[PDB]
Length: 290
Ligand SMILES: N#CCC(=O)N[C@]12C[C@](Nc3cncc(Nc4ncc(C5CC5)s4)n3)(C1)C2
Image (cartoon, rainbow, N blue to C red; front, side, top):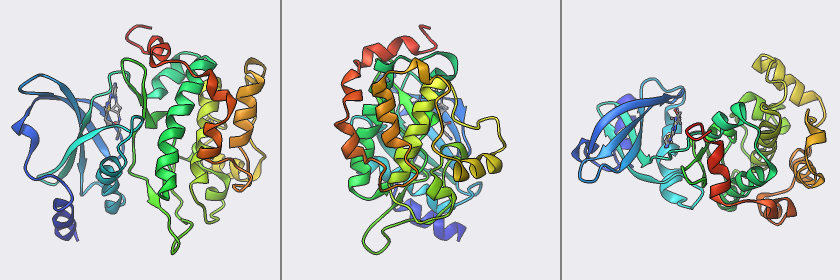
C-alpha cells in the first residue's frame, strides 16, 4: 500500500523538488498532519509557506489527497493559495502563499474582536463555504485554527485535510470527523450529514470570537461531545455584550435540526454582515502591532 500510495500521489502532484527555487527552509508551526516552514523565492525572496507531511505518520493516508486538490480546484479570494505540490522522499510538500497575520486562534485567545471584525471573518468564511458546498464538498474542520489572516486583514480558509464530498449516490457522509468542541450534534450522534455541519461549526467559531473559547472547552473531548449531543444550542457567556443582529445571525447557525439550519447561501444575505469592515480593520488585532 505504501508504495501503491506513493505512486498514486506522485501522479497528482507536480514533479521534482522545490529546492529548485526555494532557500531558507525554517520551521514555524506544527500540527497533527505535520510541520510547516517558511522558505524564500531564490530569485526575489518572496516568502512562501511549505507544509511537510509524512506519508507514513498519517492516521488516514487517503486524506492527503485533500491537502492538494481542494486548493487546486477551489481557488477563491478567501481560500489559501497553493502554488505547487511535491513528493520529497516520503513526505508530501505543499507550497502556499505565506499569510503574515497567522491563525485566527491567536487573536481570539489574546484580544476581544468587535462585531465589525467578526462580521468580516464571517463573510469571508461563508464565501469560501458557499462555493465548496455548491459542489458538495464539506469542510468538516471549521474552527479559528483553520482560518488565516494576511498582514492587510483579508481572511482565508485553510486546513482542508478533513474534506469530504457529496453527490446523488452518496448524499450524506457518515464519518466521525472534526474537532470535538466544533462538531455538529447530528455528526456526533452518528446521523448521516451534509454541509450543514460546517455552518454549526461556524457558529461555534463565532462563540470563539466573542467568549474566547467554544462551549465545554474545559471538559475532556468525549464528555464534551456527549454534552453537545444531549443539550440544547449553547449560550453565549457574553450575550449581554453582543448586538441583536449578531444574535439573530448566530441563532440561524446553532440550530440542532440541520434542515432548519441556515445555509451559507442564505446567510450571505443576513444583515449582520453589512457590519463587516475592510481588511484594514482586522490588522490591529495581529500580535505584531498589538
Ligand atoms: N498541521 C498544520 C497546520 C499548521 O501548523 N498551521 C500553522 C501554525 C502556523 N503559524 C503561522 C504563524 N503566522 C503566520 C502563518 N502563516 C501561514 N501562512 C500559510 C500557512 C500554510 C497554511 C499552512 S501558515 N502561520 C503554521 C499556522
